[PDB]
Length: 215
Image (cartoon, rainbow, N blue to C red; front, side, top):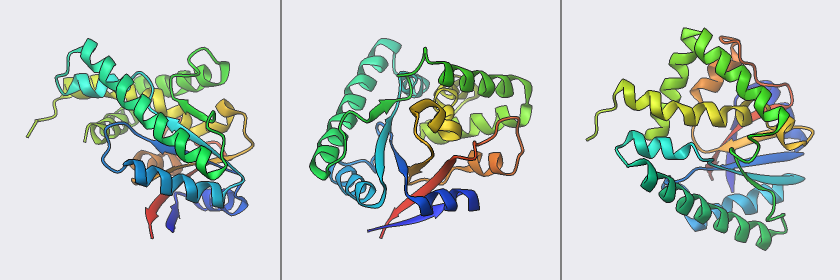
């Protein structure tokens, strides 16, 4: 009951093998009602050998702060929303035979070698390469989406993009799985640019991007 489109042909090859999908669930996004989460997870468990879930880490507060939410309140709001996201994912995983413990936020690995190494690569590109930095700021703009979005707002919001990107380029390094697709319902423009080798940053050969749409 879901249609799929892959980012590259290599992504499609991973898709065909059905080993693992990493289901992205983002906070304060209206797509992620309890019922949608249940349907999406049911689909994932049916289609793939293994299913894991990715939630927003601490940097989600930056998105709120960029919109004028005081930092203290922003941190509490994120904790509430992410804990809610988790509870829905846990319930859905349990119900369909998945593992409720296979739910991670992008902050859970701050002290892990694999994650840190990927953060370093992304940060180096961000500071070194104007083209990559601009693409990231644009990604962070999308993450925030009448308030006018300012440069200062994006400089705050972009920490979110930097913190999550390791899971978009090499989640298997971090999670220890053989290969995966990050599944999400929006297109990923930065990923399109990454796939055309426009940046120092590369998507790993065992990482794909899967855009899912209700059928």
